[PDB]
Image (spheres, rainbow, N blue to C red):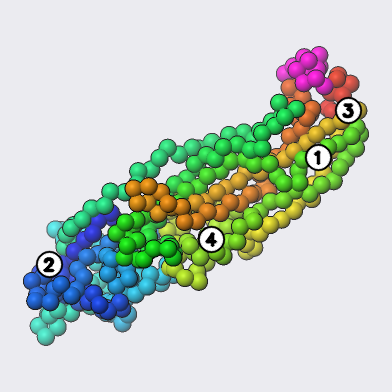
Amino acid sequence: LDTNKVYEISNHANGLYAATYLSLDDSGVSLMNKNDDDIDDYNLKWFLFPIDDDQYIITSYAANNCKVWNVNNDKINVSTYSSTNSIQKWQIKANGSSYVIQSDNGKVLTAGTGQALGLIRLTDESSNNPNQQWNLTSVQTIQLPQKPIIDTKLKDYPKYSGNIDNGTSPQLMGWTLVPCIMVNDPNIDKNTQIKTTPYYILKKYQYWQRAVGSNVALRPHEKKSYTYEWGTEIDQKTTIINTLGFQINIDSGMKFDIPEVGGGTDEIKTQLNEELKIEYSHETKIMEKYQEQSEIDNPTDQSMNSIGFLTITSLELYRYNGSEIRIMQIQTSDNDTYNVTSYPNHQQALLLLTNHSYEEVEEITNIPKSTLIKLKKH
């Protein structure tokens, strides 16, 4: 189904609409006649958000604090979204001209009859029960932010000219839309949130940046030990975990948490993996700030300078109101991407030697032939 619409949901058999009481935040869901004398005290508007595996979350649209349909003992009420609560997940299955609405528990939405006319419950699906068929009527469509051009290849890390850049420019490597119900945005109310920014934009940028501590000066014929920093200096608790319900582990892979406030994004993890190209973590340790011991060897008779780069990943989340408003960012660096480069560039010299002569390389790199030979020696 389209998930950028506000829908009314009505029963095929009895023509009544699914509704909550506006003034009770934890309201049960009932069936009301759209011309009832008190219809203005109910909400009939529902917003569908898509989650993994062709399922949906059904959200009270700017009513009941944007709580979502929630099944308890075969009855439906609206409760705070929880990305770890299976009883809030739905399947909506086309069945001729209507739809069957099925809970994660396998039962289906059913209108009561007779003394129970007006009631809605979950029960077992029957062969053909008009009371288990539902119509979705679109009453509003919200135009969504358009996905921009995404890069697929990270530019090379900088090389010495002997000057060198401190990094490269951020490239957008992934972009995806996140249901507002899965976003804890403490600076806006939930009802205003769903009306103005029902989908947030989550971007992933990558680029290279100099590793702090990695600029090393070497004299002739010496090895020098050093340490560079990597990881993140950002507090994950107050940024990504409390906002989206996930953390970045030492692996640079993502790990899903139950946030202090908010429902989280556990139910869209496949979408995140695929659209942001972020691996699931294989570690248990959250990324912090680290120092990797390393060594530079200069086996030549000339001095040398070295510096290292890391691939930075920046995850940034934006409200979208006709423009993007950033509400969260975190940058991390991945020690498995560490690369060093030198001046004079011994690595470029050895590579050049695979299809150039010594005299040619000597000319290109300014490195003497005897050194070129020493270099090749190890």
Tell me the CA gap for discs 4 and 1.
34 Å
Query: Tag on residue 216?
Result: 1
Callout 2–callout 3 Cβ contact below 8 Å: no
User: Which residue bears the numbered disc 4?
Assistant: 239
Separation of disc 2 and disc 3 at Cα? 85 Å
- Residue under numbered circle 3: 302
* Residue 174, percent from left and from top: 47, 45
Residue type indicated by callout 1: Val
Seen as rendered, the residue at the extreme front is: 187
Q: In whole angstroms, how far apart are the C-alphas of marks 1 and 3?
A: 15 Å
Separation (CA) of disc 2 from disc 4: 45 Å
Q: Which residues are magenta?
A: 355-367
Labels 2 and 4: the sequence-earlier one: 2
Query: Can you say which quadrant of the picture contains the N terminus?
Result: bottom left
In the foreground, 288 or 275: 288
Q: Which residue is mark 2?
A: 12
Question: Which amino acid, mark 2?
Answer: His
Residue at 15% across, 72% down: 40
Kind of element beneath mark 2: loop
- Residue 357 falls inside the magenta stretch: yes
The amino acid type of the residue labelled 4 equals Thr
* SS for dot 3: loop
Cβ–Cβ under 8 Å for marks 3 and 4: no
Where is residue 88 shown, x and y percent of the image?
A: 35, 70
Asked if the residue under mark 3 is in contact with the one under mark 1, i.e. CB atoms within 8 Å, the reply is no
Mark 1 secondary-structure assignment: strand
Cα distance in 3D space between marks 3 and 4: 47 Å
Query: Does residue 86 appear anywhere in the picture?
Result: no
